[PDB]
Length: 69
Length: 122
Ligand SMILES: [Mg+2]
Ligand SMILES: [Zn+2]
Image (cartoon, rainbow over all chains, first blue to last red; front, side):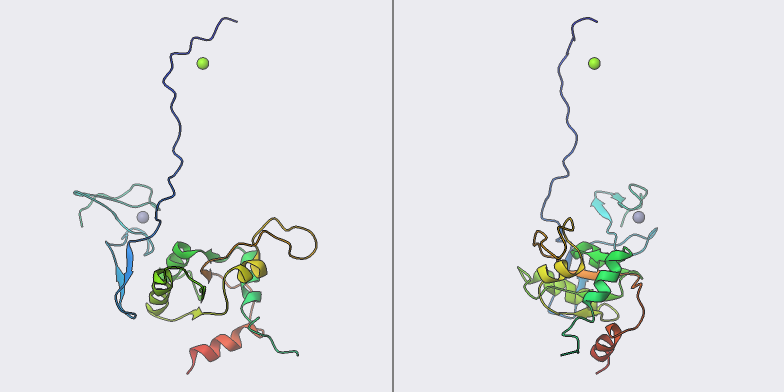
């Protein structure tokens, strides 16, 4: 064996980031159940569309979506 | 005393835990509600912010109401299963179960369904 070279550049993974969890669902005045954004057509409700500038995707399908809404 | 003091839901929860038919937490509960997964619903009475509770209520309303209040979350957790067993009886690290929703059911009829039926039919 020889000496280890080490050209630096140490990269770490992704630690999720805990965040505020849920905000994309609302109740107006009790009775009126109100949704933010839109649900997935490929798989049933419980999945929201990820809203960008003419870019949409879902997490149960991991990525598979494209159409603007 | 022989009558169940709202123990006609704890048993159900236990059964669900056993056969992995639990939507535990808020998001999971919501998911269960939105389609044909969640059939019974239990929420915390000591919800912080109240917004969460409101959301749960809204979800329950959607088409058909499965909600029942009972009492707290920690107790529910203790009943169902939170912690690495620990000795003969209970002694687990006491943390709340949050909003708990039943999938699958598993067990049939018993004293479990009568109270729920009563709640439904008014
Ligand atoms: Mg190397
Ligand atoms: Zn999807």
